[PDB]
Image (tube, rainbow, N blue to C red; front, side, top):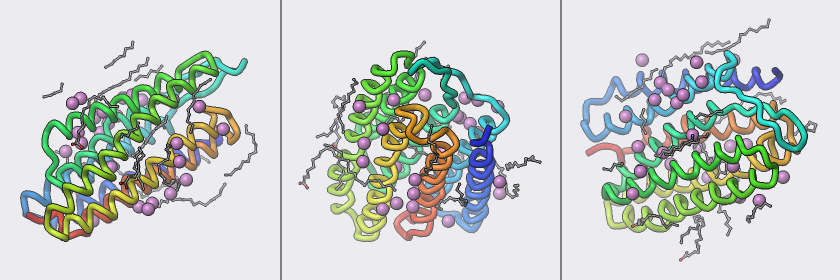
Length: 225
Ligand SMILES: *C/C=C(C)/C=C/C=C(C)/C=C/C1=C(C)CCCC1(C)C
Ligand SMILES: CCCCCCCC/C=C\CCCCCCCC(=O)O
Ligand SMILES: CCCCCC
Ligand SMILES: CCCCCC
Ligand SMILES: [Kr]
Ligand SMILES: [Kr]
Ligand SMILES: [Kr]
Ligand SMILES: [Kr]
Ligand SMILES: [Kr]
Ligand SMILES: [Kr]
Ligand SMILES: [Kr]
Ligand SMILES: [Kr]
Ligand SMILES: [Kr]
Ligand SMILES: [Kr]
Ligand SMILES: [Kr]
Ligand SMILES: [Kr]
Ligand SMILES: [Kr]
Ligand SMILES: [Kr]
Ligand SMILES: [Kr]
Ligand SMILES: [Kr]
Ligand SMILES: [Kr]
Ligand SMILES: [Kr]
Ligand SMILES: [Kr]
Ligand SMILES: [Kr]
Ligand SMILES: [Kr]
Ligand SMILES: [Kr]
Ligand SMILES: [Kr]
Ligand SMILES: [Kr]
Ligand SMILES: [Kr]
Ligand SMILES: [Kr]
Ligand SMILES: [Kr]
Ligand SMILES: [Kr]
């Protein structure tokens, strides 16, 4: 399986990212700051587990569509189901979002990843893209609440919080927006690029969205109470 190279590198970078965050957090006692270390280290730990599972051949299924048997890594969606809500919780704790907003984001993130997977398992080529469209609408709902709602909340807090939140907000909009496009061009969608290139592109986005995001958050004074 040519994609195995990117599964192995993906596992190695998520694993080292998780260990990095844990070692950096050992120099921290602030209760507020520890909550962000715990969440931010768990995200690449979950991704490490799912990349290792896919590398060893677990979390793969064949879906017939477009008159072919198509390899679909469903473990990718299992990873995203747990990690995308932890990343949204990092942002929600930074701007001290209320519990209702937190539930609405988790729910919307559940629809985004759930309909993602339904589309990936859909046997009628055409309907794959209806589910992609619903998943994308849910992502746009999330990015709207983050970009407009959370910025407004962050601007009513201390400037250190507004400043860190804006950088994390900018990275999230850019990286999250790439995912639906990679799905469209990859083996899950139109099959313009082969599985091994889809895997490489998801791996770069995942490492950027977990380790990159995590470095920006945990280097900031905004996480201290
Ligand atoms: C750690 C990984 C992260 C930040 C993953 C993000 C994943 C997405 C934003 C996925 C979104 C998708 C759509 C909006 C369209 C349909 C397919 C998905 C699931 C790739
Ligand atoms: C600049 C990046 C913004 C990304 C988050 C929003 C994603 C798109 C979702 C729905 C459309 C929102 C309408 C945007 C108009 C701008 C309004 C304003 O700046 O006052
Ligand atoms: C056929 C794979 C189903 C995915 C389980 C969440
Ligand atoms: C699906 C679009 C979400 C934006 C809310 C105004
Ligand atoms: Kr590797
Ligand atoms: Kr550690
Ligand atoms: Kr956590
Ligand atoms: Kr996991
Ligand atoms: Kr895990
Ligand atoms: Kr596994
Ligand atoms: Kr799995
Ligand atoms: Kr799983
Ligand atoms: Kr998982
Ligand atoms: Kr988990
Ligand atoms: Kr969460
Ligand atoms: Kr996020
Ligand atoms: Kr959240
Ligand atoms: Kr909710
Ligand atoms: Kr929910
Ligand atoms: Kr979720
Ligand atoms: Kr899922
Ligand atoms: Kr579409
Ligand atoms: Kr999808
Ligand atoms: Kr960015
Ligand atoms: Kr970015
Ligand atoms: Kr986009
Ligand atoms: Kr998109
Ligand atoms: Kr496409
Ligand atoms: Kr990418
Ligand atoms: Kr990227
Ligand atoms: Kr980043
Ligand atoms: Kr860090």
